[PDB]
Image: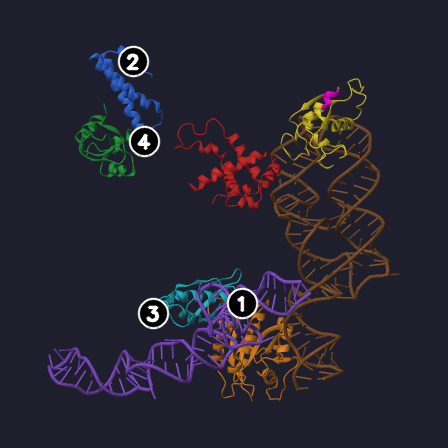
Chain colours: A yellow, B orange, C cyan, D red, E blue, F green, G brown, H purple
RNA sequence: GACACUAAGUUCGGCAUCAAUAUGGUGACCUCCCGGGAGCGGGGGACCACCAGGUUGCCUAAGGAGGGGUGAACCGGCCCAGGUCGGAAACGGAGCAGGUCAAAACUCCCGUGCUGAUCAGUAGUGU
RNA sequence: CGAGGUCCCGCGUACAAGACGCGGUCGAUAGACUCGGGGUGUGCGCGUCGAGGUAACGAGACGUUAAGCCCACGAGCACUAACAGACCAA
């Protein structure tokens, strides 16, 4: 029941039809499922990385380009896990904003 | 169907045309348009052909051959046998286009080369005219500034053509057109 | 494809006489190259033999050569007549 | 001259005569234990996958005197073939290397 | 290697000769294989020679 | 101590000599000569040597062409090695 | 007679052939939402290109919403085997090869504009 | 913003390279062919004669034959080649 977050969703180098889900203004260079998980897990979000899954609209097969990330929004009872994270859009955006800060990118 | 008479100016197209239709002589002037009339053939069934006399003038010869060629069952290319020696090049050049036009046709018309004006003493024979015309068309297919004549590697000859081509002799001045009426009958 | 009369052989007298034959062979090649822009210069052996008939020194003043062009690229193939 | 289409065709003929396969085991001269075991089903599935990769190639690449060369000069072509056949870039270079070794021996044949 | 000096001295005069004619044969067959490219194992065709030398050396020291 | 026979010489030429003239070709050492080659050959392959012809090389060895008797005949002797 | 100039004739290429609009399409791209565990399902705006037949500018000497072709390894659009990806599945997606085309682009041949060249040598005028 | 020029091509009244001069289809610049003008001295073949010789054979003579062969000159002649096209330039 967790939700799905594919890097294509947060890629500013992709068009709409190519899988982008957020405005280019907020999108990111080349987000990696890893980075996505690393910023989500570090906010109190319950999430696990599906390293080998591949996004259907992703012609490339490389690594930097594949993997999937799963985050728990609601809890079995119904309450959101983190009030500040209603929707999926909420997480996508939060991620798009925090990755360009990861030390590994400011390097 | 139609039998087209073509050839340089003064080769005798109109006089032959008259002789075939009336058996008589008549004065003529350079033709400026085509003329036509029905000819009842000499054979038993007496088939009818439409003889069409075409002007030989350079400014009209092709315009009119183009206009009537698809209606032709046969073409009679008339040659002044007495003036042949000086006119060879002009004759071959016109015949060249006539050979080409004829072959590009769905049902190629039968073609005769009527060596006319035999009644004049200095007249070259049909045998000699055929020989000199072959030699001349042979040079023309090379110098001629894709349908072509015979085989490129073998000296040109009328027999190499995908067309029935005959040569005969005649005189429009009564006249001596027996062979011509024989051929016209034969192709009717 | 046409028949042509190669002089340029006359020019071969401007070279000494014991070598006229090679000069000849070159002139024919250049003649047919020229006139005849679309004409490569393969010279059938018959032509070579013609010029060399009376030896290296006694080339004729003229040769009649039959030559053929194919049209695309500019070749020529040429022989004696 | 051994092209990539030629290799494609040989693969078709080899797969076709595979079943058949019972009769072949009933003929002497093939030494001891002729086709036993047992790796004829896996082996044919391999040829079929290579065929699917060549299905992503075009006529120029297939009828080229040296199909491997056409990809050395235009490595962009390798990427396309791989995309269309659901295979990786390395898999296509592997096929190309195998084709190279195959064609070598065919002229040595 | 596989055949040591102690083991050669251990053997009887007759066993050295029998061992000798044995090594020669291994050798001869190795050279045949090498003919006729030999499957092998270069370290041995060389050892066979030294083995034979040792045996002959010992046969001499012992007085046969 | 050195051995007489070194190894068979296998070559196209050695094959023709085996098949058609019935001989065997060996590499021996240099100074075996010729008697010694004949004897060595016999005792190794259990045969009758009719003649031996020898050549130094170059190879740094020596080559011996050893012809056997007709009943020995040679294709067979060589086949077992 | 011999030449010129305008009008003009023949022929093969001769040269040359707008602009701005509504409605409906196709495509591309962006931007907002709802639903959903994925592949997605659903709905609102914006921009650009092109097409179908339809106007008008007050537009040029002419300028028709004509008819083909090619479509390129990929790099136009469709349909997409196989394989690939998401899916337990049902299916769905990206998509090469292959096929295809009112609607990327590029090109011919057609009426109309310029326009090389060719042939004729007539009509007038002038020397 | 096109006067001219270089390259180019065919040749020399010019010339070791370079330079110079001429012509380039609105053309006779070079070659071919024909003729003119020239050089040698009468061709191959055949016919007759020929000292003789059974004959075979036969040096040579005459005729055909001002022949034959040849020309670094001229003319006629666009057949062939001077094409195609490039570049520089206030």
Crowding near the residue tagged with mark 4, few <14, some 14–19, many ≥20 C-alpha atoms within 10 Å: some
Residue G120 is left or right of residue F77, and the answer is right
The x and y percentages for residue D85 are 60, 36
Calculate the distance from the C-alpha at mark 1 to the C-alpha at mark 2: 101 Å
The x and y percentages for residue C31 are 47, 67
Q: Are marks 3 and 4 in contact (CB under 8 Å)?
A: no
Residue hosting label 1: B148
Residue at 26% x, 19% y is E53
Residue at 26% x, 22% y is E24
Crowding near the residue tagged with mark 3, few <14, some 14–19, many ≥20 C-alpha atoms within 10 Å: few
> In this view, which residue lies farthest toward the top?
E10
> Element at badge 4?
loop
Span colored in magenta:
A39-43
Q: Can residue B153 be seen at all in this image of the molecule?
A: no
Q: Chain of mark 3?
A: C
Badge 2 and badge 3 in a common chain:
no
- Above or below residue B105? Residue D107 is above
- Above or below residue D80? Residue A76 is above
Residue hosting label 2: E5
Q: Are marks 2 and 4 in contact (CB under 8 Å)?
A: no
Calculate the distance from the C-alpha at mark 3 to the C-alpha at mark 4: 66 Å
Residue hosting label 3: C54
Badge 1 and badge 3 in a common chain:
no
Residue hosting label 4: E36
Q: Chain of mark 4?
A: E
The x and y percentages for residue G72 are 62, 48
Q: Are marks 2 and 3 in contact (CB under 8 Å)?
A: no
Residue C11 is covered by the magenta coloring:
no
> Element at badge 3?
loop
């Amino acid at each position: 029941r967790f939700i799905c977050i594919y890097p294509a969703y947060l890629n500013n180098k992709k068009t709409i039809a190519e899988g982008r889900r957020i405005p280019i203004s907020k999108a990111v260079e080349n987000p990696t499922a890893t980075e996505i998980q690393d910023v989500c897990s570090a906010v109190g979000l319950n999430v696990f990385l599906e390293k080998n899954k591949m996004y259907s609209r992703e012609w490339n097969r490389d690594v930097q380009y594949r993997g999937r990330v799963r985050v728990q929004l609601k809890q079995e009872d119904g309450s959101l896990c983190l009030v500040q994270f209603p929707s999926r859009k909420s997480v996508m955006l939060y991620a798009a904003e925090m990755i360009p800060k990861l030390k590994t990118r400011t390097q | 169907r139609a039998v087209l008479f073509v050839g340089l100016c003064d080769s005798g197209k109109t006089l032959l045309f008259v002789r075939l239709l009336t058996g008589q002589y008549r004065d003529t002037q350079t033709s400026i348009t085509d003329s036509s009339a029905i000819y009842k053939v000499n054979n038993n069934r007496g088939n009818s052909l439409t003889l069409i006399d075409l002007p030989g003038h350079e400014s009209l010869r092709f315009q009119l051959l183009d206009r009537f060629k698809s209606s032709a069952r046969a073409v009679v290319f008339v040659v002044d046998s007495a003036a042949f020696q000086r006119e060879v090049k002009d004759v071959a050049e016109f015949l060249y286009q006539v050979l080409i036009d004829s072959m590009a046709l769905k049902n190629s018309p039968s073609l005769l080369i009527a060596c006319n004006k035999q009644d004049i003493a200095m007249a070259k024979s049909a045998k000699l005219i055929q020989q000199q015309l072959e030699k001349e068309l042979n040079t023309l297919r090379v110098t001629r500034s894709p349908a072509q004549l015979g085989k490129k590697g073998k000296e040109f000859e009328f027999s190499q053509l995908p067309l029935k081509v005959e040569f005969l002799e005649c005189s429009a001045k009564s006249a001596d057109i027996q062979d011509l009426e024989k051929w016209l009958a034969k192709i009717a | 494809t046409r028949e042509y009369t190669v002089n340029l052989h006359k020019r071969l007298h401007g070279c000494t006489f014991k070598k006229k034959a090679p000069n000849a062979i070159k002139e024919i090649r250049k003649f047919a190259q020229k006139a005849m822009g679309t004409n490569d210069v393969r010279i059938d052996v018959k032509l070579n033999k013609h010029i060399w008939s009376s030896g290296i020194r006694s080339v004729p003043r003229r040769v009649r050569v039959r030559i053929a062009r194919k049209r695309n690229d500019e070749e020529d193939a040429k022989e004696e007549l | 001259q051994f092209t990539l289409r030629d290799m494609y065709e040989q693969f078709q003929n080899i797969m076709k005569m595979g079943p058949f396969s019972q009769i072949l085991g009933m003929i002497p001269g093939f030494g001891t234990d002729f086709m036993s075991k047992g790796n004829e089903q896996e082996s044919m599935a391999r040829l079929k996958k290579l065929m699917t990769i060549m299905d992503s190639m075009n006529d120029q690449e297939l009828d080229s005197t040296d199909g491997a060369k056409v990809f050395s000069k235009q490595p962009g072509r390798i990427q396309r073939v791989a995309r269309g056949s659901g295979v990786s870039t390395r898999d296509v270079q592997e096929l190309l290397t195998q084709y190279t070794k195959f064609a070598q021996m065919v002229k040595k044949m | 290697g596989k055949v040591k000096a102690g083991e050669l001295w251990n053997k009887s005069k007759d066993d050295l000769t029998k061992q000798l004619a044995e090594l020669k044969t291994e050798l001869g067959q190795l050279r045949i294989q090498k003919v006729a490219s030999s499957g092998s194992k270069l370290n041995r065709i060389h050892d066979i020679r030294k083995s034979i030398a040792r045996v002959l050396t010992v046969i001499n020291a012992k007085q046969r | 101590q050195y051995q007489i026979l070194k190894y068979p010489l296998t070559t196209e030429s050695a094959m023709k000599k085996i098949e058609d003239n019935n001989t065997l070709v060996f590499i021996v050492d240099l100074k075996a000569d010729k008697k010694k080659i004949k004897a060595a050959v016999k005792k190794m392959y259990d045969i009758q040597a009719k003649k031996v012809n020898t050549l130094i090389r170059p190879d740094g060895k020596k080559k011996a062409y050893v012809k056997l008797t007709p009943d020995y005949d040679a294709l067979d002797v060589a086949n077992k090695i």
